Image (cartoon, coloured by chain):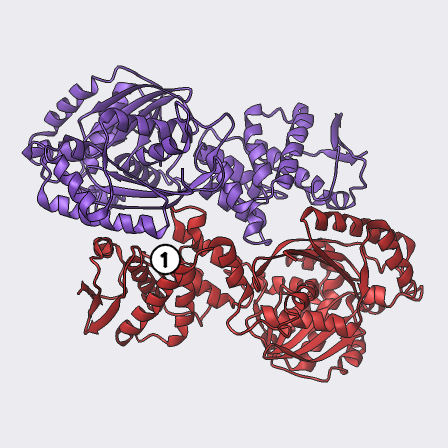
Chain colours: A purple, B red
Amino acid sequence: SAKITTVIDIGSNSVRLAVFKKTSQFGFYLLFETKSKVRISEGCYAFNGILQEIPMQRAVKALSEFKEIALKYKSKKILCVATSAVRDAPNRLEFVARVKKACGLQIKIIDGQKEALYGGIACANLLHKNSGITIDIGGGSTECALIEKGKIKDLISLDVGTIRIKEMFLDKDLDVKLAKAFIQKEVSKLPFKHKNAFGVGGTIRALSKVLMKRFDYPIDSLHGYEIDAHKNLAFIEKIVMLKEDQLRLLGVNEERLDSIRSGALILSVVLEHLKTSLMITSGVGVREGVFLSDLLRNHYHKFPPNINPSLISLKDRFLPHEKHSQKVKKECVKLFEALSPLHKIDEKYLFHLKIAGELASMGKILSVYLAHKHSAYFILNALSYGFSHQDRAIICLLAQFSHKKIPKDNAIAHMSAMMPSLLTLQWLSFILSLAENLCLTDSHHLKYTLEKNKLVIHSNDALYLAKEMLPKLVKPIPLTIEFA
Amino acid sequence: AKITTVIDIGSNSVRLAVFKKTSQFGFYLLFETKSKVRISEGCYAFNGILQEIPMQRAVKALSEFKEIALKYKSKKILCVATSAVRDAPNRLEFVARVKKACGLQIKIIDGQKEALYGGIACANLLHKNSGITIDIGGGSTECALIEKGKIKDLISLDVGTIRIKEMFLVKLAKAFIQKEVSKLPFKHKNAFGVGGTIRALSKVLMKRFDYPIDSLHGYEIDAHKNLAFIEKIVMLKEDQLRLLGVNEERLDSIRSGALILSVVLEHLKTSLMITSGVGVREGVFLSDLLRNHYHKFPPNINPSLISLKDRFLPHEKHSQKVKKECVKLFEALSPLHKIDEKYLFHLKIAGELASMGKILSVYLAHKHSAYFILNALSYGFSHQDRAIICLLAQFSHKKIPKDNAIAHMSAMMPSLLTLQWLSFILSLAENLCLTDSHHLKYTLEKNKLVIHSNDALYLAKEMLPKLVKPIPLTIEFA
């Protein structure tokens, strides 16, 4: 296993490259990513899958430069897989040899089961829910993996894809009704159902962006975006029939216009069949699954319990000294417990409080001025694997507003109907703030009790600075705070 | 040391700064805190002898400051004391008491030394290096004359906000101050405002002008235009000051501070005051850092630019390539854009820093790079220069909006068209540097730019349509 690993995926629509960098045993992050839409499948579907010359030439040229990029980052391992368009191709051996000849890259053609597995491995490890069904919609095929509690159960690969449907129906000028009936037949082959889906791939990313723009969503990242599938199913169905200009007005990018409608059609049929309630947009897929297969060597390729690669790598990069963050987290927990009779907050939020406690001072790596704002910025933007947007929102807010009143008008606080109340957020940010004050100095054996409305801080230390600072805390409710 | 803590003991408060040195010249301020222990409380009536309860407060605070220094693993701890302690007949008692409690060894410095440290900071860390520092404290006021980063002269005035609040709180107080201020031997068009009292006054002026940038450091004030309002602040009742945004702790000193400042500015004949976020603590640190360099960074050495790269850009090969192509493209396209070469400064640095944000996330990396620049490129850069560099990065491969706040932060800012040109040039340079390309050369023929290469540059060609052009222009690959 290597410190710098490049994974290249040759799909039916585009070729894509990811460079992953190890920061610790389980910590890693995505160092670089790029894609080229070479559409190697262009014109092949009428030819019984034979890859056409011009598309093959485009693919070779892109892949040669992907090799250059891999070497630029000094990758010690370079892994290359090819999916539906290449595996289906009668001339696949010719194409593989041409790439090896030009680029030195050895393509591993993977079957649909393996493709579904790699997607499943990524989603089972890197999302904020571990039970659900992946939906990976590509140009030539669509894969679903059923995951139960982090374990891959079943796999299905279907030959329906955005470009396949485009070229066999929407080009030959067969009605949308015909395309739909054909997709429905293939989708009937999926035996399972689940409330959760993990959306994988470019079609689903593009459609996610459409919904974010349509609804004025406050958060920029794609990974961990939660879509109400029922609520949005009709609109996804409507996209199928839109003109390209209507797609442009929804913010669809120029290169996405020609495949997004067949993609929406496949997605709508699949969601309906799986009986999906929640779709999580996944920024991860086959490339991550290939990397995780190489990173984690044990039978199922799973992270050990309570190991999060994104939280770990964030600390590796920006917080290599862990003592202070740990102590603040510990006092946050003790304070939350002592104050629980007053606040009555659901213990599920201890998850968010603990991580805010660890990361609140991360932003000092940038500047002392507005350090908490910077931590929040880092949290919202860089804490990805294993966290929902809602998770990041709560954590970001606790840090950002430390020693401050949270405004009634904050957009992130309102990002969903399921967000905690302002009062809950203020409680949690207050607890973090007081923990920070108490942990400023070298202070051991802190203990907290609640006597009536009164929080009592027990310490053997003088705590001079913490006493001085007490009036600058913003309390969620009037609360008497005393030092024994 | 890698981590150095500097503690300074003033009349009103004790302050701590922890500095992290990332390379030979790179460093940044890691942590800071203050405690207003008012060690000088009631000491004037007593012949300047520091009273028991105030000394007890100082010792408790300093003890915990020591703990903080150790929690940051500081390998060097430097502690200086200024006018209140300096002037105290029991200063030896106090120094011994502090050493007994936490082990801290206090170095009492005189007024000239205090002026020197403030001067070293302002000489190195601001975007102009010629001028006169003004450091207004509770017990004294220091001024250092700096010429091109070198310190020419030093003086410590026996006037501070405490005594002026005591004796007077305008024609009278001003009369007393003037007596001391007349002792200033020098004048300059530039002043560097130092200290929390002047920073508080600067916040008031920044809030009232609606300033798009947050940093106090490097904030420029027109000394003539704002003198009236500075003098006004002196006569304001506490209630009004509170409305102007003045923090609770600074209400006692901000009026007498405003009075001293107005007298000094008039005497120095200052036309421009640059608010400094640095002072004695940074000066003590730099005295050590620069001891072998004559207390000045060598030419083209900027500690913030360097420390930014130390933190976020460990490998510079790619960014030096982008910079180099930025310059070559600028010079090839100059007949068309006709842009002032002074902006090559900003373009080169945006070229160096554009991919910095990738360390945070590859998604929206340019937005992160911009965020880093705006917030962390601080020492030695003017607000305008920083804003330009931020914009070029932020808007790579995009159209810059007409209403942009940062772009409009002043009338000396470049035009939207100039900004779009520079952002476009950066964007094209980034495209050409994606792969492992060999020597590139550019030519211009009317509105046609020609890229000459022995490389296929397949990806760069594919990406071409995603570039946002400032004018109609033809880009071809030879």
Q: Give the position of the N terminus of chain A as an image quadrant.
A: top left
Furthest residue in direction top, as rendered: A191
Q: Residue A2 lies in what quarter of the image?
A: top left
x, y (%) of residue A289? 35, 32
Query: Which residue shows up at 81% across the image and 33% down it?
Result: A484
The residue that disc 1 covers is B395
In this orientation, does residue B210 appear? no
Q: Is residue A69 above or below residue B118?
A: above
Foreground residue among A162 and B299? B299
Q: Is residue A178 above or below residue A245?
A: above
x, y (%) of residue B401? 35, 58
In this orientation, does residue A194 appear? yes
Q: Is residue B288 left or right of residue B209?
A: right
Q: Is residue B327 above or below residue B246?
A: below
Chain hosting mark 1: B
x, y (%) of residue B377? 51, 61
The three-letter code of the residue at mark 1 reads: Phe
Furthest residue in direction right, as rendered: B46
